Image (cartoon, rainbow, N blue to C red; front, side, top):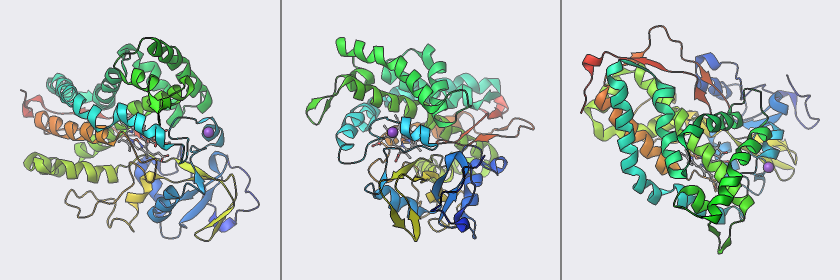
Length: 405
Ligand code: HEM
Ligand SMILES: CC1(C)[C@@H]2CC[C@@]1(C)C(=O)C2
Ligand SMILES: [K+]
């Protein structure tokens, strides 16, 4: 239900949006969030859902808030409040100045140089998975590709058993789209329960995996503590297991449904990177936020100290004030404007990994399985949260239309 309105919040700003179960979910998750950008809805509304919080509805406000960490702190970045208070991943839960020393370490485990070195494993895995599926004439896209392809790479990188995937993924999802059986805090603590012994053990006898590197790293010239290492490793796991995994299904769903757009990429493969980018805008999927460090007036609205404000990364590129005809996918879009990977000082650090992962998928999939569709009569269900996703994507094709090598 709906938390009672705080004395400081005027009635005309109330729009009761639930980010975990939005009213128009059936029409598509990006579409359900876009109801916040209809003509009679303010730039800045208060929802009585999920304990009560603000939502900036437009790119300009979202951008401004992300830049202004002095008023909009990451210390409590998740809705509901219990989740933001329990949230303590590094660097995400820290503001500058302290946040920054940690980014460099994180970079050492997921940035460009790590990515260049993983690139042949990544390509190899995409081809392997796709060739395996090709002759079946069908798949459950989420289980058979969108999960194993990003996730086996991350486990490879982190030096963790593939048999640990289901427990890890379960826990991760409880932190972005809870089924209601675990609080944020309960899942985080269970994530820590798993990491703690491994981090110590990798501090005792370091390897060349990501956990060893974080575990034995330095932070602006001094050693990382055990507790900090854990709070960093947890964030990497979440990003490894619940970002690209969901993005791929939005993109594949779209491609299953538009043969023209497939044909465009088959016919002009040089368009793939630009296509990646337009799809990143279109099927944007993250929505975290910040907390007010003081009473502050912002675009003519009075915010109180401790108020939570959701600043949906998803919404900036769907905003018609940033991109005309924003629901329309155009790979030749002259100026693709979005905040898919964030804005300000917390700007995504796995974005090179993610764009490689996307681009490789587009290429290797259309190469082998050019014609394909949604299974007969399947109604694709989406799910909303910190990171939205797709419940299931059953796909079909005629193997005769496909090409191996
Ligand atoms: C489609 C893919 C992805 C999207 C849309 C995405 C989105 C984002 C967003 C919106 C933020 C900012 C959070 C905030 O400002 O509070 C962020 C930060 C971050 N992301 Fe990504 N992400 C993606 C893939 C990945 C991957 C694969 C990783 C690998 C681990 C990753 C690692 C991180 C890390 C470590 C941060 C924290 C940086 C900081 O707080 O300074 N992301 N990401
Ligand atoms: C919003 C995010 C996608 C960003 C990386 C993982 C995530 C869930 C975070 O906790 C920070
Ligand atoms: K916190």
